[PDB]
Length: 583
Ligand SMILES: Cc1cc2nc3c(=O)[nH]c(=O)nc-3n(C[C@H](O)[C@H](O)[C@H](O)COP(=O)(O)OP(=O)(O)OC[C@H]3O[C@@H](n4cnc5c(N)ncnc54)[C@H](O)[C@@H]3O)c2cc1C
Ligand SMILES: [Cl-]
Image (cartoon, rainbow, N blue to C red):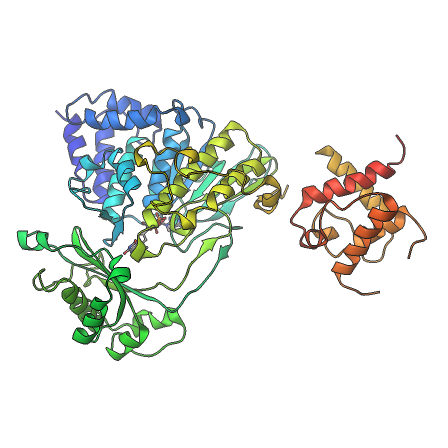
């Protein structure tokens, strides 16, 4: 039987190319075209009615039938480009596809090559337990196992995303946005190496960027923040799965709070000074440690004391042989030798798998979402995963906060598909974003099994109006109400003839306060240089109030920052209302 011979190969595939190989071999044996969407998910399960595999269809159909998605129609008029086939990219891709949306994902690499091990919060375990991971990965969180290697997380999620009919492409980097030439024309992706001509023509109205710690799309800004110099070191050793190795208790890291006698012993015993060390028993014996610069220099792990941290941990300044020595001795002391002699696993390049990372930064994007609109054509952009907020690896928030963000973005595209105003969608979304960087299992909802896209199911005492529509206008970039153009033409008419006033808009035009003075001076002749925009703005607001009867809608600061156009429009409307030509 050809059918689910393929399907068993597909399920147990450990290599990206083979998952891909298998699926399109399963598809051919079924008359199903790969790239989906749900319609092709349907014909797959409806033509493969074999035991052991039904367990999986039950799990997926269980999630697929829960009200939020309705029945894959919530987002049928929604077309997405998802960037990044990382875990958060795939996890979000699955939600979009379950929502019924057309999901096309682009990934720059062609293999899952990372072997570092991620901590999984209890809810993510449930979440992907119920996506059928146990079947795609036998060792998935067996017993009290709390973690999963990056590439295994990807092998799972890929298989789920493929099944659900996500059109995925490999070996193609999203470079930027190629905007609409004209109404009716949509947004497209700039891709490279320049894609096939149908991907090239693919027009979308939602972009979800899950591209990892170093790539955010245009217009998204990054708030950088740096703590004390902090050097992270990960390492993977061959885990032979002998009974002896299997008994070595793993090290959680929370012991740095409860146990510092250890770090003293480590230091005395090896000359190694760590701030923390973590050990997970996974496909490899995984260690991540945090080290003091002084310590790494003294041990010849780093060649020279370099001030620019990116050059401090550049290839030229990291001594491979000494780093290996360093990691080996630390791993060995911490597990008291019970792992036997440690042999480095290979990384994907084929090197002893040990690397140093900058752990100093606390990056967050300023917002989780924005909306661009040109020639009436709207594009919702949503951040997910490491690119949104950077995880502190020793504390294991990466998967969980990436997943929370992926649910919040799918929830966002649901509002977007309901027809909500861009400001409303953004405000709601930024209200959720606010909570992300302080989430813990402890301050979240207790019942992880009842978790769904609805943020209420996840965040206790949820305030969906923490950020208001007025506070996210700079997130809505309208670079393309007919009463606004009346107001504008009228405002321009009033302030005409003033040296260095040129009313052009309802933000930057009015920022230095001279526009306001002109308006007032014009409206009441005979009242009253180089004081700042602050004094100009202020006089105008006081004089408007007392002479013209119009109280301030915006503060002076808000006039100068120009980030509240709607409120300036409402201010100005009072002047026009008060002094319209006639009735
Ligand atoms: C080398 C490396 C080692 C790590 N080690 C640990 C660890 O030890 N412990 C821990 O807790 N976390 C670790 N992390 C972070 C962890 O991998 C992520 O939190 C987790 O995978 C979820 O992140 P993500 O999907 O948002 O981003 P990522 O995992 O970075 O995935 C981003 C995806 O986007 C692809 N991509 C990037 N740019 C583009 C582009 N322009 N166009 C198209 N595709 C693009 C990338 O190839 C990648 O596949 C590591 C990350 C990296 C990159
Ligand atoms: Cl692979």
